[PDB]
Image (cartoon, rainbow, N blue to C red; front, side):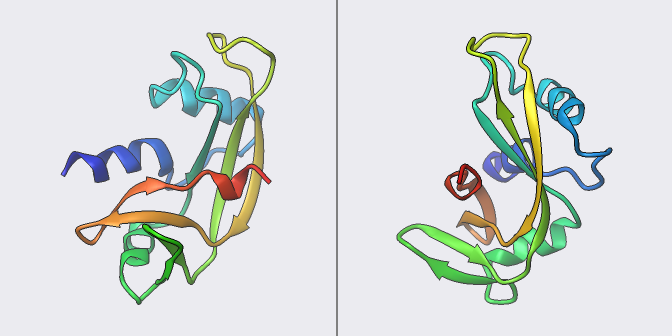
Length: 120
């Protein structure tokens, strides 16, 4: 359903343009995440083949209550809001990382990214 589609929109970017502040400012705006400014957001890179797999044991282990945590590690770019105001223009800071990810899967597909692990 739409929740998978909405995971992609908010947390999938196949091929990032250099993953700096300006990329964050750009892709956030583009994906509808700037009114008001989404405080923190993380984009997974690579193929979807691999992300959806976190819903099976091909690439996932159960985790906590409702979630799944990936076996593989993914390239990732966390956009973090900075400045004070919740309202555009939304200035962001990009942090590129490389680690496994945590999602909730509903009906074999990811419908939620847990952002907690990208704050610390």
